[PDB]
Amino acid sequence: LDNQIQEIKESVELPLTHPEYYEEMGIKPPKGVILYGPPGTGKTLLAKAVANQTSATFLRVVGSELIQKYLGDGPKLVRELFRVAEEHAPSIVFIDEIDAIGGEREIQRTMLELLNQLDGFDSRGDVKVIMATNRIETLDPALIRPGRIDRKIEFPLPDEKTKKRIFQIHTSRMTLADDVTLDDLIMAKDDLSGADIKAICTEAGLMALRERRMKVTNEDFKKSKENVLYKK
Amino acid sequence: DDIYKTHLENNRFGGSGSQVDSARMNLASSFVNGFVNQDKLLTDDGNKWLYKNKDHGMLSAAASLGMILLWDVDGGLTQIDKYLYSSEDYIKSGALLACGIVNSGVRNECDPALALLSDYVLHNSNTMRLGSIFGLGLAYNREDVLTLLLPVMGDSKSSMEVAGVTALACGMIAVGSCNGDVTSTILQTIMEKSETELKDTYARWLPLGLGLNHLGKGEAIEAILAALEVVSEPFRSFANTLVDVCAYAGSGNVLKVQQLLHICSEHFDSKEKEEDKDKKEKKDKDKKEAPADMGAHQGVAVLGIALIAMGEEIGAEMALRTFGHLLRYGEPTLRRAVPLALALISVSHDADPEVSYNSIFAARLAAMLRQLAQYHAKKGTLTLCPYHSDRQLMSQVAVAGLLTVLVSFL
Amino acid sequence: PTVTMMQVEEKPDVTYSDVGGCKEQIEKLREVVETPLLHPERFVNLGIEPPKGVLLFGPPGTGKTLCARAVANRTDACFIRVIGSELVQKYVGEGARMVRELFEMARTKKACLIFFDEIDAIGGGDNEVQRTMLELINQLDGFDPRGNIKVLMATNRPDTLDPALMRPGRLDRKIEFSLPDLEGRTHIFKIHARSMSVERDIRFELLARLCPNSTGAEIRSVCTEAGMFAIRARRKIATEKDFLEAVNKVIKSYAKFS
């Protein structure tokens, strides 16, 4: 995913960073990109959202829970996002785990309000909005043609290779034994996303916490596998 | 190298020089001319621009050519020579002011201004004393300029800026002295200060130069000497608290910080302004404790005191976060006071709060000060004096003739 | 409501010479947007019922670019572009007050010009649409708002029967898409030379002759894969030898099935 991360890096890191080939070029795509992946779970999407945290302002709003937890006030918080995104623009607007549509007719008018209001109706574009969701087919087609004009990226299905690589990244911070092999894991699993391997990591470190040990023998790795293997 | 390595466009001369009108934003266009900088188109933009201007605006615009020519010593004489000894008093007095602004080591412009000086009532050479005593103070323990200043303070003109640029000029001559001095210069201006109890602005800008002569101390007992011989009813208590401000430039002396907390609640609402305004001078290095609850107060100026306490620092997100609340105010002196530090603290984020001010208003002071802030955007005493003298902007436009000649701007 | 202050369109956009190659048709649609704007009394004194505007239909191609051109050629006060998706909505009854309040804004804005986009969404059960199109034509044929300012329909299908039989009375100057010849694309090239770093070694006549049947949509996709594959190749300058595969790919791989 090196090209997939350097294309979002070069895509959204062109404004306000390395500006000698952005404002002199006369392009200015002030719309950001749209992220989605079959694994989802915000692991790769947060590993790509963290690639922009180096020199920028980060703003993470996960899901529409803060909207659907009270009376239907509506797009007023989105207008607040337009006044804070207008009076203060370094911040890339990063929205992860978009499960608003999944009332519904008010999500269509705050979707038309963020679509219409996001284009920069009063200025020459003002804020980059990177969107991240789990499924791209459930979203209404109103955000596609008017909103997305620059680029949207798709995540391929590895089946084996980035299951091994995602295992390597999930187990990079953790400690894996020598006898813990990878072929039986990437092979024994059948269409399991990053959340399930994050769950077997969760039973690895959590079941290691059950015995208050930092090391996980193979026998304790299958006995630890039984924890979420029974819980899931 | 500035003309070589930098390339500024013309749409700010034309645009920023196009939103000016009503003879006050025209003064903001003298601010455009003097504090715009490569390109010098607005400098040579035809004529009659100074003829439409006012009198103190003729001082500010005559000094604007002094601000555009901080270089080209040989060109300064052949550019200001047209405005020298002209028909209009403010053209020649602001022209000598320009001669004092353009350089600080020429010292050959003195004689034509110094010879004319004596007026003894009102005459032009007292305004040439404004621009030439102030501009020579910018050019400068001399022992001929103060002997020439003896009939200056002895004259005692009704114009405030006479003693203004006298005290400030001799103070800039005296800043950095060896543990200060209590000599007959500032003793003489203390006795002649208390001589006439009129126009308390004298009692405001004379302690400016007093405390400037107090600067440079390491162990001076001048706070106790002034505690003896400058203490009176509240017409010299501002001088006492000014010597208290300038005598405590800053060290580890938290006893004066709890003294600051105790005397902060004084009924007099000016020693609060300057004595509480000393915070940006005292703790200027350990700026992590400088954010305080001064904005949460409910007095008359305290929010202005913290607003000045921002200053011209690099201005991290917390400072602009304080400018979020300080930016929105209803009084014209605080809404007028916010763009100064708002644009000094930031020298795609500069012009956005300016458009926020356009959303605030759309008076004249706020518009002139917000364009003046556009031009602002685009322990050295030389950067500490000009604004501590500028803390008295809430007056007539005559002071705004001395507002344009601040040397703190690099 | 929000459609009042939102409807007013500012921030001008794509200009004149982006026309997709029309030399005479750009006059046939220019002499009604630019010529009447220079003086009202001129076409009023030109006789009887001066022409309102023109009619655009057929294949989309370079659509929405000539309307942006009309917004660009506005000399004094940035104009507007009514969209079709606002008339046909849920809770009927607001489209009538909508079209009457925007025509009222046309009365308030000293003979403002109005453009109608996507007429097929309100053209052609459909009684709630018959309110918007029969009341719409009832307000166009009406002399209340104005009868000289502007008519311009930009859509994909001319299959709207009722507007086709009500249009010959008031609407006039219908034109086709007028696909360009070989020499027409180099104008769109010369104006889009602001695109992502067209090098001076790139010849616009070579790029024009290397793509037949390449109307404004297909060369707009030439620019889309040009700047897109310019960003994706980690390059900063564009060279005809670097993206000619994207040119003949975007015209041939997309001209096989279509």
Image (cartoon, rainbow, N blue to C red):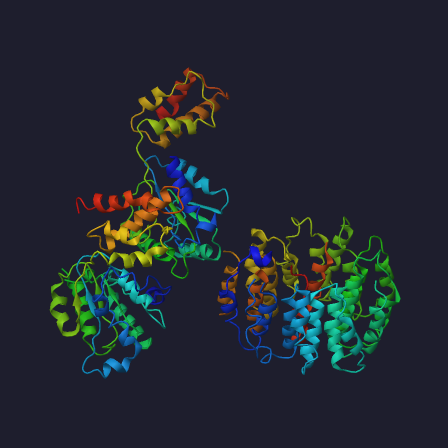
Can you give x and y, in whole percent of width and height, for residue A110 in the image? 34, 54
**Which residue is pictured at 76% across the width and 55% down the height?**
B249
Q: Nearer the viewer, residue A116 or C225?
A: C225
Q: Quadrant of the N terminus of chain A?
A: top left
Residue A166 lies left or right of residue B266; in this view the side is left
**Is B32 drawn above or below residue B6 in the view shown?**
below
Q: Is residue B405 visible?
A: no
**Is B204 drawn above or below residue A106 in the view shown?**
below
Can you give x and y, in whole percent of width and height, for residue B59 in the image? 66, 75
Can you give x and y, in whole percent of width and height, for residue B309 in the image? 66, 57
Residue A61 lies left or right of residue B390; in this view the side is left
Q: Is residue C61 visible?
A: yes
**Which residue is pictured at 43% across the width and 41% down the height?**
A49
Residue B219 lies left or right of residue B404; in this view the side is right
Q: Quadrant of the C terminus of chain A?
A: top left
Count of numbered badges drawn on the protein: 0
Q: Quadrant of residue B22?
A: bottom right
Q: Quadrant of residue B30?
A: bottom right
Q: Nearer the viewer, residue B6 or B362?
A: B6
Residue A213 lies left or right of residue B319; in this view the side is left
Can you give x and y, in whole percent of width and height, for residue B329 in the image? 56, 65
**Is C231 drawn above or below residue C81 in the view shown?**
above
Q: Nearer the viewer, residue C92 or A35?
A: A35
Q: Quadrant of residue B276?
A: bottom right
